[PDB]
Amino acid sequence: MNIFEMLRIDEGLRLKIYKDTEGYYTIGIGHLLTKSPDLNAAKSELDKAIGRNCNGVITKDEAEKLFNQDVDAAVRGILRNAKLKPVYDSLDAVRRCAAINQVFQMGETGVAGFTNSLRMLQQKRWDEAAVNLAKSRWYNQTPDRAKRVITTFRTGTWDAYK
Ligand SMILES: c1cc2sccc2s1
Image (cartoon, rainbow, N blue to C red; front, side):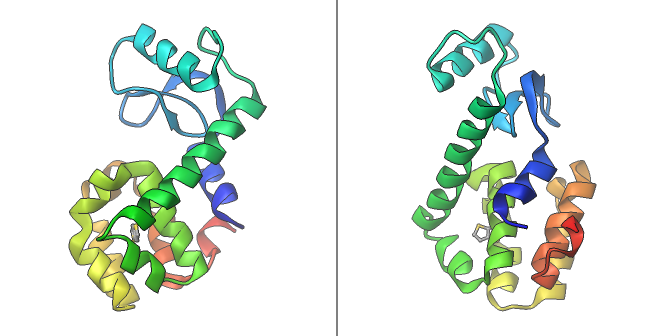
C-alpha cells in the first residue's frame, strides 16, 4: 500500500466525465473539473488540463497523469500550509497518507475545519483524534471512506485497505 493505491481505491477510475459524491463534474481518479453545473464548463476545464480537445473522455494514461499531478500538488500544499505542515511532519509515513487522502478529498479549505482533530493528531492521541474526526460533515456524507481514513489515522496501519 502507498498513497497512490490508497487514493485509487477511494476515488475509483472513470475515463468519462462523471459527477462526484457532491454532484460536481470530475474525471479520472478523483480529478475535480469544476463546481459549475455547466457540462460545457467542465469540458473546457478538461481540455485545458489535458492539452487537447477531449470531448469529455480521456485515456487511462491521461487519468494517471492528472492523478500524479493532483497527489503532488496535495502534498506540496500541505507543506506550504502553516497549520498543516507541523502536524504532517509529526506523523509517521502511513498516517501522512491519511492526511494526503483527506486533503485530496476536501481541499485545504475543508481541512481547516479540523483544528481540534489536528491538535489531537499532533499530540498522538490517536483514539481521541479518531473520535473527533468522525464528528464531521465529511464523515456523515462519506462514512465508508472516512472510516477507512480514520482507521488509518487511528492505527498507523493499512488494515482498512487490506
Ligand atoms: C496535514 C496533516 C493532516 S491530518 C488531516 C489532514 C491533514 S493535512
